[PDB]
View 1: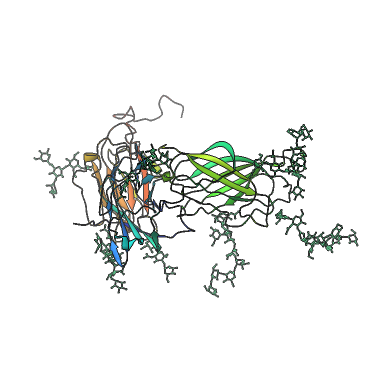
View 2: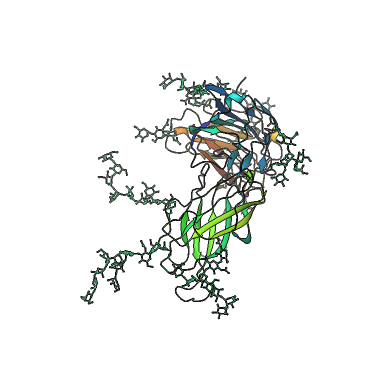
Length: 440
Ligand SMILES: *[C@@H]1O[C@H](CO)[C@@H](O)[C@H](O[C@@H]2O[C@H](CO)[C@@H](O)[C@H](O[C@@H]3O[C@H](CO[C@@H]4O[C@H](CO)[C@@H](O)[C@H](O[C@@H]5O[C@H](CO)[C@@H](O)[C@H](O)[C@@H]5O)[C@@H]4O)[C@@H](O)[C@H](O[C@H]4O[C@H](CO)[C@@H](O)[C@H](O)[C@@H]4O[C@H]4O[C@H](CO)[C@@H](O)[C@H](O)[C@@H]4O[C@H]4O[C@H](CO)[C@@H](O)[C@H](O[C@@H]5O[C@H](CO)[C@H](O)[C@H](O[C@@H]6O[C@H](CO)[C@H](O)[C@H](O)[C@H]6O)[C@H]5O)[C@@H]4O)[C@@H]3O)[C@H]2NC(C)=O)[C@H]1NC(C)=O
Ligand SMILES: *[C@@H]1O[C@H](CO)[C@@H](O[C@@H]2O[C@H](CO)[C@@H](O[C@@H]3O[C@H](CO[C@@H]4O[C@H](CO)[C@@H](O)[C@H](O)[C@@H]4O)[C@@H](O)[C@H](O[C@H]4O[C@H](CO)[C@@H](O)[C@H](O)[C@@H]4O[C@H]4O[C@H](CO)[C@@H](O)[C@H](O)[C@@H]4O[C@@H]4O[C@H](CO)[C@@H](O)[C@H](O[C@@H]5O[C@H](CO)[C@H](O)[C@H](O[C@@H]6O[C@H](CO)[C@H](O)[C@H](O)[C@H]6O)[C@H]5O)[C@@H]4O)[C@@H]3O)[C@H](O)[C@H]2NC(C)=O)[C@H](O)[C@H]1NC(C)=O
Ligand SMILES: *[C@@H]1O[C@H](CO)[C@@H](O[C@@H]2O[C@H](CO)[C@@H](O[C@@H]3O[C@H](CO[C@@H]4O[C@H](CO[C@@H]5O[C@H](CO)[C@@H](O)[C@H](O)[C@@H]5O)[C@@H](O)[C@H](O[C@@H]5O[C@H](CO)[C@@H](O)[C@H](O)[C@@H]5O[C@H]5O[C@H](CO)[C@@H](O)[C@H](O)[C@@H]5O)[C@@H]4O)[C@@H](O)[C@H](O[C@H]4O[C@H](CO)[C@@H](O)[C@H](O)[C@@H]4O[C@@H]4O[C@H](CO)[C@@H](O)[C@H](O)[C@@H]4O)[C@@H]3O)[C@H](O)[C@H]2NC(C)=O)[C@H](O)[C@H]1NC(C)=O
Ligand SMILES: *[C@H]1O[C@H](CO)[C@@H](O[C@@H]2O[C@H](CO)[C@@H](O)[C@H](O[C@H]3O[C@H](CO[C@H]4O[C@H](CO[C@@H]5O[C@H](CO)[C@@H](O)[C@H](O)[C@@H]5O)[C@@H](O)[C@H](O[C@H]5O[C@H](CO)[C@@H](O)[C@H](O)[C@@H]5O)[C@@H]4O)[C@@H](O)[C@H](O[C@H]4O[C@H](CO)[C@@H](O)[C@H](O)[C@@H]4O[C@@H]4O[C@H](CO)[C@@H](O)[C@H](O)[C@@H]4O)[C@@H]3O)[C@H]2NC(C)=O)[C@H](O)[C@H]1NC(C)=O
Ligand SMILES: *C1O[C@H](CO)[C@@H](O[C@@H]2O[C@H](CO)[C@@H](O[C@H]3O[C@H](CO[C@@H]4O[C@H](CO[C@@H]5O[C@H](CO)[C@@H](O)[C@H](O)[C@@H]5O)[C@@H](O)[C@H](O)[C@@H]4O)[C@@H](O)[C@H](O[C@H]4O[C@H](CO)[C@@H](O)[C@H](O)[C@@H]4O[C@@H]4O[C@H](CO)[C@@H](O)[C@H](O)[C@@H]4O)[C@@H]3O)[C@H](O)[C@H]2NC(C)=O)[C@H](O)[C@H]1NC(C)=O
Ligand SMILES: *[C@@H]1O[C@H](CO)[C@@H](O[C@@H]2O[C@H](CO)[C@@H](O)[C@H](O[C@H]3O[C@H](CO[C@H]4O[C@H](CO)[C@@H](O)[C@H](O)[C@@H]4O)[C@@H](O)[C@H](O[C@H]4O[C@H](CO)[C@@H](O)[C@H](O)[C@@H]4O)[C@@H]3O)[C@H]2NC(C)=O)[C@H](O)[C@H]1NC(C)=O
Ligand SMILES: *[C@@H]1O[C@H](CO)[C@@H](O)[C@H](O[C@@H]2O[C@H](CO)[C@@H](O[C@H]3O[C@H](CO)[C@@H](O)[C@H](O)[C@@H]3O)[C@H](O)[C@H]2NC(C)=O)[C@H]1NC(C)=O
């Protein structure tokens, strides 16, 4: 019996230049709860290929995610494909509340191929994500024009001369970042800068290129430029800054004109393995930026440094009340539309230790009063507002983490923090005054 998943996200993808052969899909979209360290996630992907007119499925099983422990994941088994296919795919957690999936091309994951059908296509991708609260989140990303996986294990070419500028390039979330120093003879004012990279490690060949053109008038100190690495561009664009490190016209000897160069290119897959080599090409020309003069090269390493900001953002609200059961009104689902046919309030007692018990409080337009939800109350109010009644009365400010989500999947997470019990004034049983011991 196949998935139901409330909340499905569409996503168009296309290939820019020929690929380095990763093939990468990122998903700013799933829920990673803030102030939650026990929050597992049940990921299950599914690629829909095409061989001849024939459409062939491939279900991968990533099992359970442990965001507070593991950053990178590999499917643990996969029904419907070749073998040694288990490490053909790669699901990596990234920055703020998001995922990326990298399944390499040039190594067919479909054995179902007779020599005849050497030609294989990748039509779309399904990434299932079952919530800690048990909400299945689907994310169907579809290749604009089918992408052709064409086996190869060819060219194991390194580049040649290139002065090694020992400085290591490190990748964090598929985003590389290095600052290489470089000097350009003949560049005071009349300098045309043109950089071009190419991370050539492993069976992977990424190739980045300035797109908006060259920096024709290289002003002094921090020129920012955009670059387009071949593959599947990331929402966080990829750029670089050429900053100057030498006087205007005030040098004359050997040291031509010094510059500090910083590269920030994106989709740079771990598949590239560590000990790959970043080639940086540059000239001081405008006639043929192509294959021009100087080449500088650096080694790259893939940190397994679990991204920091993994949990989704928060807007805390402080309440203080006395009635021994407070009430917050989770405002409108997303914004301006009191006619969604799918709202979902969702409660949380901050930093919960146990999954089988702490994630039971949930509401919907058609539900009401959830099974295991102890001491939290929730029911919709006027204009789609949602009042939550917290009655777990203590004398130590509990912070509740609410999450609401529209039919659009525009999640929004509050973080109310009930100061609760302010406490009775000492003279509670008396305090009836009149000026008698004071002038009047
Ligand atoms: C990297 O990429 C980089 C960027 O993409 C690139 O820069 C780099 O590559 C190369 O770098 C080279 C330098 O390193 C550079 O040369 C390359 O770029 C260009 O070169 C071409 C070709 O150049 C020339 O060859 C011509 C023929 O041989 C020659 O006419 C030119 O000029 C002379 O000056 C010498 C010095 O006196 C003289 O000995 C010569 O005999 C000759 O007269 C030059 O040798 C250029 O064509 C091209 O561009 C134009 O732009 C440049 C820069 O602006 C000019 O030098 C050139 O003349 C031409 O431009 C003008 O064009 C527009 C359109 O009309 C004008 O509106 C604009 O303002 C500009 O001109 C002025 O010139 C007019 C014509 O003479 C004047 O009439 C005008 O008027 C005046 O008003 C003023 C106030 O408003 C004053 O009043 C002034 O004054 C005098 O005033 C006194 C009293 O005060 C009195 O009244 C008197 O009567 C009066 O006369 C008025 O005249 C105004 O002055 C390029 O710029 C470059 N490559 C490229 C493609 O960029 C790349 N690197 C690599 C390695 O890849
Ligand atoms: C590194 O990467 C970075 C990211 O890529 C990059 O940064 C980007 O740089 C960009 C610059 O290219 C920036 O985009 C711009 O930013 C300026 C800031 O405002 C923004 O608005 C953007 C779009 O809405 C938005 O994306 C941004 O976030 C931002 O908020 C903006 O001012 C810029 O300029 C204008 O100029 C561009 C370029 O030409 C033009 O496309 C825009 O329309 C706009 O210019 C108009 O207005 C002026 C004055 O009125 C006119 O002089 C212009 O001619 C033009 O206007 C019109 O004439 C038409 C004819 O009469 C008329 O139709 C138009 O009106 C309405 O226009 C509608 C569409 O625009 C539509 O056409 C509508 O429709 C009817 O249409 C039908 C048919 O459809 C019929 O024609 C009908 O007749 C008609 O009525 C019209 O009525 C106008 O009046 C520019 O947008 C961006 O900020 C930035 N991004 C980021 C995140 O940084 C870096 O640069 C890269 N780094 C390097 C170093 O390169
Ligand atoms: C990998 O990296 C390496 C290094 O990081 C890159 O190396 C280099 O490639 C470039 C080309 O890309 C070569 O280019 C030109 O080089 C010259 C000269 O180089 C020096 O030669 C001096 C003089 O003698 C001669 O030797 C050369 C070559 O054999 C012949 O061409 C001549 O005919 C002549 O025989 C020599 O004096 C100078 O230095 C000495 O220093 C050493 C060590 O200190 C001593 O052993 C020696 O005794 C000398 O002592 C000196 O030391 C004292 C003490 O400080 C000092 O007082 C003295 O004054 C003296 O320095 C070198 O050995 C360079 O002149 C050219 O310069 C032009 O560029 C300038 C910089 O921007 C600019 O300011 C100038 O105006 C010139 O510019 C213009 O050229 C353009 C383009 O052609 C024109 O369009 C424009 O209009 C102008 O004409 C120029 O740089 C380098 O020589 C080469 N370096 C090495 C070490 O090999 C390599 O490229 C890179 N590879 C890749 C793929 O990126
Ligand atoms: C909160 O509210 C929202 C809104 O109400 C709810 O969202 C709705 O959610 C429900 C389910 O919960 C969705 O059903 C519903 O609609 C869309 O999805 C269904 C399913 O679509 C796709 O899946 C089909 C099932 O397939 C799988 O099948 C394979 C093999 O068969 C299995 O092995 C897999 O394991 C897997 O499970 C596919 O068959 C289907 O299509 C095939 O077609 C492809 C392209 O045409 C082809 O290339 C591919 O190879 C496949 O073979 C697809 O992948 C759809 O049925 C609905 O779509 C219609 O459009 C289809 C495509 O255009 C037509 O084929 C179909 O006849 C439908 O009819 C059309 O209507 C249009 C416009 O009115 C008209 O022009 C046209 O003439 C047709 O009559 C649909 O897109 C969404 N509804 C909305 C509004 O988005 C949400 O569930 C709820 N949440 C909560 C909390 O409960
Ligand atoms: C499922 O996957 C399996 C395996 O992944 C697929 O099947 C296999 O078929 C491969 C060939 O197509 C076999 O080749 C491996 O071993 C090679 C030999 O090993 C190094 O080779 C040196 C030189 O070679 C010969 O020596 C042999 C023994 O002496 C001899 O038979 C032969 O005649 C030659 O004389 C040898 O001296 C040295 O001691 C060592 O044996 C090796 O060259 C193969 O390539 C590698 O390349 C990949 C890609 O990087 C790496 O992942 C591998 O670990 C391995 O090693 C490196 O190469 C890197 C890049 O150059 C380098 O940077 C790095 O440092 C390292 O040295 C290959 O390993 C397999 O043995 C065979 N496997 C099995 C189990 O039978 C199978 O088809 C797949 N199935 C499907 C459906 O897809
Ligand atoms: C703050 O919020 C809390 C919850 O969010 C509000 O809830 C009250 O809190 C207490 C717990 O702290 C609940 O126990 C309370 O409960 C029900 O209490 C009744 C029990 O009745 C009595 O009689 C027996 C037998 O003689 C006796 O042994 C016992 O001690 C007691 O005296 C239930 O009967 C009642 O349910 C019934 O009544 C309705 C209407 O007729 C029926 O439709 C129901 O089916 C059911 O039979 C209560 O549910 C709970 N109180 C209420 C009224 O909700 C708390 O009120 C709130 N504080 C304020 C002031 O807002
Ligand atoms: C999220 O869910 C909302 C509530 O259902 C959608 O309205 C919203 O919208 C796409 O958003 C568009 C912006 O209003 C809207 O667009 C179109 O058609 C009109 C009429 O020709 C044009 O004026 C607009 O330019 C626009 O193309 C669509 O209704 C909407 N699509 C759907 C199916 O809702 C969703 N937003 C997101 C994140 O997708």
